Image 1 (cartoon, rainbow, N blue to C red):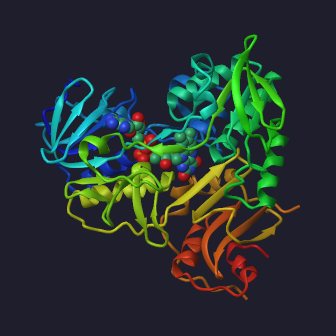
Image 2 (image 1 turned 180 degrees about the vertical axis):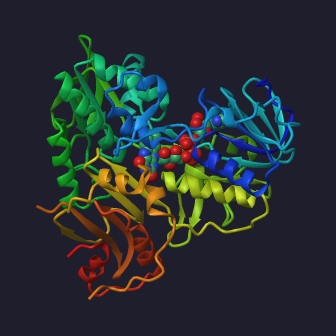
Image 3 (image 1 turned 90 degrees about the horizontal axis):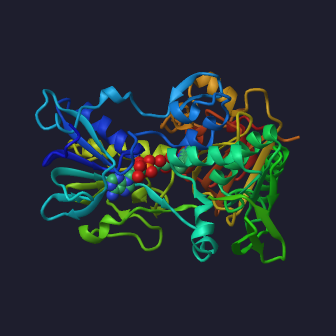
Length: 474
Ligand SMILES: Cc1cc2nc3c(=O)[nH]c(=O)nc-3n(C[C@H](O)[C@H](O)[C@H](O)COP(=O)(O)OP(=O)(O)OC[C@H]3O[C@@H](n4cnc5c(N)ncnc54)[C@H](O)[C@@H]3O)c2cc1C
């Protein structure tokens, strides 16, 4: 029943967010389409954001089993994109009436033969295709100190990516006295807050350490990076900025992290959250171009790597309408680019002109959104205000019904943006020559279309305090 077919019209390599969106797209445009997703994981397609967020905010002990979570508004949602009975079997796929979408789980595509329109799986199965999407996502970066420390340290280090890592780390959280997160980024900070909340109830320790001066310091300016660090500290987490890891070893049963400044940190387990590299292993056999500067498969405006091979999601190095070649790690991009790839695979020939958004929540009470070029080394103007009662992720989730912020923001850009005639929220403009090239929104929701319009228009702005009024910052 899960026997690989010899041929499929639409082959999707990888079974994450972009592949699911593509399958949906293909099927909407061609209701008899036969679509095979090949997924190296055991699980059917699922979304990632809850893995560092709402799944940790449950008191139900069978969360690890069901992977149902409660949104910030109390409403239950499955991590899976659709119920498992909505897929057809791989065996049935070639000739079942009206086609369908099948998933081969626990199978990895290891070779791509582009001239022959064929892939080979790790078990030796050969599948030919008519149209192919590469949607392989990324592979977490390791830390060189872990790489050089050997197998014992490696075995006590988690690179947090999938359902399996949620399960392993949630178990570690219940069982050990101290966990250290290495990395200042959004994922590391979400995990710090999640683990920190668990630890408060157990009386245990969570450390977050990183070389930057504060959380998300590569992206946020000092004021908001510092504020974030304080929020994380308010959760009980021990945050160690300006920490440069020299080495990691085991000392009488504990991990011992040595920092350049002379500090030594003893802990039971390490989570490394220091980014990823696109999964481009198939470029070798496929002879496909990869981007040496940004990583990822190079694609054209229509997301094509070849006449009949598209790329979407984290794996794609696309041409951003404003910024040129880039890759992102955004749920929004994976949805929109996967949907577009599917449309183009069914004859749309439409260009990828979407401006991808990003969001992060540090619990129900603090959220961020970002769009465009967001880099703390650029000149910035931050405009802040006291928060109102609605300016938090929980309220945004209550109003919209969803915690997936890309859905509630919409994909749209505003049609017009006429300026109308402690701090807890604000807007940060990232600049080039008075032109806004990126925006971070701090506890401001339902305004992403305005931010997109500002950046798309690319006008010079004489007074960004006036522009901030569009974000209800006065
Ligand atoms: C824990 C976590 C939290 C996140 N939170 C947010 C958030 O709040 N907001 C946001 O904007 N973004 C968030 N992201 C980013 C977002 O989830 C990703 O951008 C999105 O998952 C990318 O989708 P994708 O389809 O490109 O890749 P993935 O969803 O990673 O799917 C790729 C799949 O392909 C499989 N695969 C790879 N190679 C092969 C092969 N050769 N054969 C078969 N299978 C293969 C992989 O195992 C994987 O299952 C988060 C990511 C993670 C990990």
